Structure formats: structure tokens, C-alpha cells
Image (cartoon, rainbow over all chains, first blue to last red; front, side, top):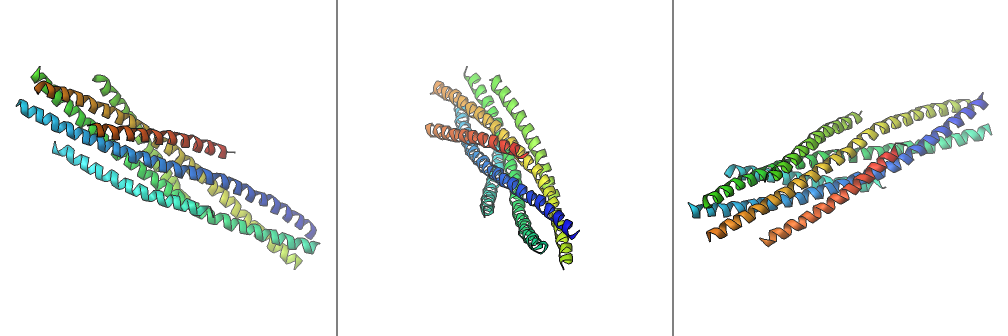
Length: 115
Length: 115
Length: 115
């Protein structure tokens, strides 16, 4: 049986030795999908940034039309909105700053992973 | 050779025993980058929410200017846009509700993972 | 000691054989959270798309009010903004096109992973 036991041991070591190579292959794949998720987020953030510039342009557009229509009505003859707009504008800038930080870390850690 | 075989077996078991510790280290790292990706998404969603409040504020701003300019033109003397705006507004609210749900699950599952 | 060594070898092979099953369980879990992160991103992108249609609707709304107020002022009696709006609009369309591509790959790779 010492004889037989070495046969068994060797068989188990081989089949499990297989498991490891399996696991390392899958782990290889998952590294790719992970970088894809990280890049996707940098993209999603840049769109969000750009959309904010767009939103700032339209608020300015609206403010100008307020002036022009106000004057026209005088020739012929609001503050809450300004607050809520200022507040939400502040928030979106925080969330963007934080999202920029979070994006640098995630990219750094993903870079560290390639060792 | 029984002697020699036990030498080989022991050598393989050691080198593969190494593989496992390697794999567990990398798996440790990847847990971090994964929480970073999940947090990043909560951030990206909150920005998107805020931007929607901002967009709602500007649509209201625009509607008011429509009233004021309409009146001024009467003193002196559209519906599709309202539809498309109502529709897209409905959609963004769904996508946000779903994104809020998806964010709770992902955070729960990520929490379950620390066992 | 040949006797004893086979006892040790068998003990190590069992405890490490455990490690593998452990690792495969955790790997099972992490596959779920990964699909959840990928779906979440498809959602975040669709919201961003919709918000862009919304932004396009409001820029058009603003342009119309510019015409109506311009005419009213003539009866009675800008180009940079148009540029910046056109530019940022172009960018957001690129970032969205790229984000759509990135989303297909990530979904494909995640699909490949289930072998």
C-alpha cells in the first residue's frame, strides 16, 4: 500500500495541478474585462463633464434671454431659481472632482496589478 | 524509486503550494480595485441625478420665458417639444430608478464578498 | 520515515485541496458582481444618452426664444455661444459613440467568460 498510496497522491496532485492552470487562465481573461470596465468609466465621466459645460452654456443662454425680455417689457410698460441652480451646480462640481480622484486611483491600482 | 518519487511529489507540492499563495495575493488586490469601481459608479450616478435636477430647472426656465414672450407679443399685436420633453424626462427617471436598484445590489454583493 | 512522509504529503494535499475549492467559490461570487457592474454601466450610458436628447431639446428651445425676442425688439425699434455649443455637442457624441463600442466589447468578453 505504500506503493498504491504514491499512485493516488500523484493522481490527485496532477488533477489539482490542472485546477491551478484553469484558474490562472480565467484570471487572465478577467483582467481584460476589468481594464475594459475601468476605461469605460473614464469615458462615462468625460461625457458627464462635457454635458456639464453644455448645461452651463444653456443656463447662461437662458439668463441672457431673461435680460432681453425684461428690458423689452420695461420699454412697453426669479431669485429661487438662481439659488437652486447655483446649489446643484456646486454639487455636480464636487461629484466630478471626486469622480476624477476615484478615476486616478482605480487606474493606478489597475496599473499596479500588471506586476 | 519509492524514495525518489517522494522527493518529486514533495517538490511539486511546494511549487504549486506557492501558486496558491500567489493567486490569493492577486485576488486580495483585485478586491480593492473592485470596490473602487463600485464606489465610482455610485458617484457617476449621483452626478447624473444632479444633472437631471439641473435639466429640470432649465426646462422650467425656458417655459417661463415662453409665457413672458408670448404675452409681450400679444400686447404688441410648440406642443411637440412639450411631448418629446415629457417622454425623455420619463425615460431618464426610469433609467435612474433602475440604476439606483442596480447600485444597491452591487453594493450588497460586494459587502457579502468580505466573508 | 517513508511511512511518515506519506502521511505529511497527504495532509498538505488535503488542506491545499481545500484552498482551491475556497478560491473557486469566491471566484463564482465575483463573477456575479462583475456582470452587475457591466449592466450598471449599460444603464449609466443609456441615461447619459437620454440626457443628451434632453439637452438638444433645450438648446433648440432656447434658439427659438432668441428668434421670437429678436423680432419683437425689431418691431419696437451671440455667435461664440453657438460655436461652444456646437463643439461640446460634437465631443459628447464622440464620447457616446466610443462608450457604445466599449460597452459591446465588455459585454462580449463577459459573455466569453461563462465557458
